[PDB]
Image (tube, helix red, strand yellow):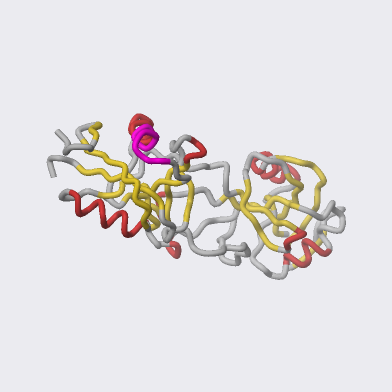
Amino acid sequence: MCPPGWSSNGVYCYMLFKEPKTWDEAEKFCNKQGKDGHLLSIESKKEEILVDIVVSENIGKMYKIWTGLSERSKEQHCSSRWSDGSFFRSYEIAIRYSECFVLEKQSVFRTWVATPCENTFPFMCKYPVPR
Amino acid sequence: NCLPDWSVYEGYCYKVFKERMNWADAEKFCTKQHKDGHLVSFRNSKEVDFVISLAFPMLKNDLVWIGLTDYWRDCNWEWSDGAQLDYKAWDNERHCFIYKNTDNQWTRRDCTWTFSFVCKCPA
């Protein structure tokens, strides 16, 4: 029993919004539509599939769509390891920081790709009717 | 300090190979060359310069694998709705570290492709 225009899956309501925003703003936007709404989280291949298809039908084309996969900013606690030592000295052209993930039209919106949070892209909201 | 055909530097031995392997095989091949050997790792004991200036002139000097696969982990990413990050659909093959000699810096690339390699084991 989801609002008009919204779709249902696994007793959850979902809606894709063709309104480009920042991770932060889209996330904020989703939390205003209904108690505990959020950028969509994807917990199964089946769900991943129910979302790309809702993207495919309601969003007029765009290369990326925001999902709620956010960086925890715990890097100093998540130090990677070489096939032995610790990953401190590093040397990459780490342009700007990309602490966000979105869905890529390239892979029919089924896969995730690390992207800059500040980028404006359509999004998919989600929330449970039982609050 | 090192076996024949292996360069010495700061207590480590380095040998260059001209084979072309994917990350995974490269690591395995390295472990096989000598005890405690692995794809070269860099911490900047000025190994870079050395590795590329001495433990490289004995190589095609391009693109060598780096022993670091920075695969996405649960430790630093999560859902805004606090749901656990079980199912994941991010690319795992992406992110194998690599050194591009022409750019004189590291880079992340498909773990599935092929590259030269420099194995390293502490003496």
Which SS does the magenta portion mostly show?
A: helix
Q: Nearer the viewer, residue B98 or B55?
A: B98
- Give left or right: position of B100 versus A21: right
Q: Which residues are magenta?
A: A53-60
View extreme (left): residue = A130
The answer to whether residue A4 is visible is: yes
Q: Nearer the viewer, residue B89 or A126?
A: A126
Specify whether residue A57 is painted magenta. Answer: yes
- Give left or right: position of A107 versus B57: left
Q: Residue B122's quadrant in the figure?
A: bottom right
Q: Quadrant of the C terminus of chain B?
A: bottom right
Specify whether residue B49 is painted magenta. Answer: no
The location of residue A71, given as percent across then percent down, is 40, 57
- Give left or right: position of A98 versus A42: right
The residue that appears at 82% across and 58% down in the rendered structure is B56
The location of residue A78, given as percent across then percent down, is 45, 58
